[PDB]
Amino acid sequence: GSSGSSGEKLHECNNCGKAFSFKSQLIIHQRIHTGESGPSSG
Ligand SMILES: [Zn+2]
């Protein structure tokens, strides 16, 4: 939640309100909102 959108908004996050100029990128970010699945860490 911080104002600072650069470049064209090709893919925006319909959860927090972020923007990504790469479909894949956006998907990688949305992971924070959803439950991921990987190795144990932290
Ligand atoms: Zn988001």
Image (tube, rainbow, N blue to C red):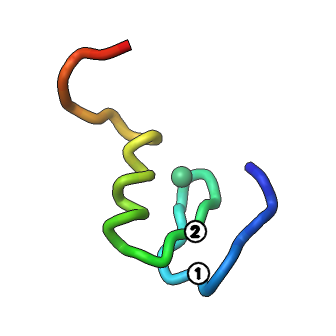
Q: Position of residue 42 (x, y in %)?
A: 38, 13
* Viewer-closest of 23 and 41: 41
* Viewer-closest of 27 and 34: 27
Write the residue at 21% across / 31% down: 37
Helix, strand or loop status at disc 2:
strand
Badge 2 amino acid: Ala
Asked if the beta carbon under badge 2 is closer than 8 A to the nearest atom of ligand 1, the reply is no
- 27 vs 40, left or right, is right
Q: Position of residue 24 (x, y in %)?
A: 32, 67
Q: Position of residue 6 (x, y in %)?
A: 69, 76
Question: Tags 2 and 1 in contact by the CB under 8 Å rule?
Answer: yes
The residue labelled by disc 2 is 19
Q: Residue furthest right?
A: 3
Helix, strand or loop status at disc 1:
loop
Q: Position of residue 23 (x, y in %)?
A: 36, 73
- 10 vs 28, left or right, is right
Write the residue at 50% across / 83% down: 10
Asked if the beta carbon under badge 1 is closer than 8 A to the nearest atom of ligand 1, the reply is no
Write the residue at 44% across / 40% down: 32
Write the residue at 61% across / 86% down: 8
Q: Earlier in the sequence, mark 2 or mark 1?
A: 1
Q: Residue furthest bottom?
A: 8
The residue labelled by disc 1 is 9
